[PDB]
Length: 252
Length: 252
Ligand SMILES: [Cl-]
Ligand SMILES: [Cl-]
Ligand SMILES: [Cl-]
Ligand SMILES: [Mg+2]
Ligand SMILES: [Mg+2]
Image 1 (cartoon, rainbow over the protein chains, first blue to last red):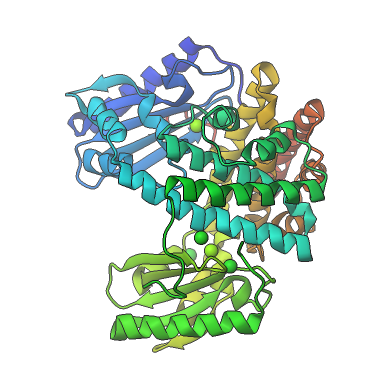
Image 2: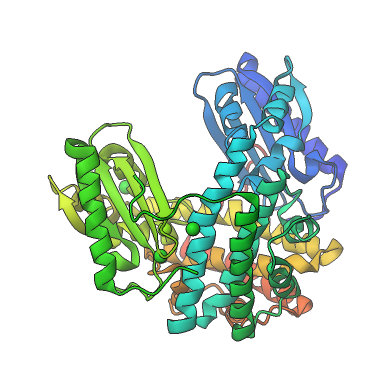
């Protein structure tokens, strides 16, 4: 019957039962246990799932348990300190979605500053990694999307244009979060938070208006908006120096 | 203002230049080079990008070159045979999207029949792997989405509902592709191809009509149709034997 309504109590009671089980099973190999996500921020909604992380001492440990009782769902990730610290300092295109984890840790067990080390690692990533991630996002995501909607314009199917427009708006939101080095709180707040940031590429606000209102049925207006945003991307990347040499056919 | 229009002949000229560069640069370390995707499928559209894969001899090789010339985009993935074969036989939630690569390989260089081995491996994945992927998709993706839209029903923001409904339709399309062990042709064809299939969960077609028409502005209607789809998922899993384990509070 899908997820049920739960109070914080009820979620925190579940969390501590899981914490006790984790300690019972893995003992001294457990360096720390934390809750993250909306429950970690104390902004969990009545229907939110439960996300937990466990820092292991064990060499190369990297596994997870994700399950449901039919009424709620839990995900517990287990990583060695070195693997987690490596992950916390890697900036991919979806860093604004994934790494909010590390700014929302509610520590529930910690044998010696491990969760603070994770947070410090996440918040200390050097600027070059964000610069590289943005340039890669332009190539690997937005340029590809531009080809996809131009293909739709000339050969269909327009039945994919609403979904593609949503994907472009989300990629634009990742671009904005990388530029400002800010992680979105929840996936539901991404567009709301993205359009509140400064220095957006032109055309992004208009695109997000279509996506947030759900008025995605006028294909000519969507293609116009996507092209306008794509033009804004060209101006924005040039203004901020997110440019690589593209003159050679083969750059290796 | 790329991507520009190119013919298939122009793309294959680019492809063979890149093949010559790879062989020039990496030499005897190159086992095979193939084109995949729409171009490998000879169904590339006027604006399609170029996707290439390279099997390397060094056992831990795993890198890529992805770039644009301003006018077109190329992605070349380099993997050792061992890494590629393992990846070709892994079935994740997005297998219907990602593993079409392995059924669209056009070999352009091959010193040992390596690309046929990759294809055979991808084709020979056991049915249990799809069963496990379906159960994981329901728990890890759909159950989470249900919580997100139920939270929206009671506390907003409805501005995320069009994007969430798109994500739910795509997850349903992965479920259908896993059930039929079929990879979608292009990402733009996913919804059209998923809804032509047999054995759809009840409510999925109705939900996809909103997403494909782009009529995503009526929030009550989307919430009703998501709930109906969620119910249809429950009946569909029982009919097809995809029983998710809900018996343990803590399964470790
Ligand atoms: Cl570019
Ligand atoms: Cl291209
Ligand atoms: Cl297998
Ligand atoms: Mg979650
Ligand atoms: Mg590509």
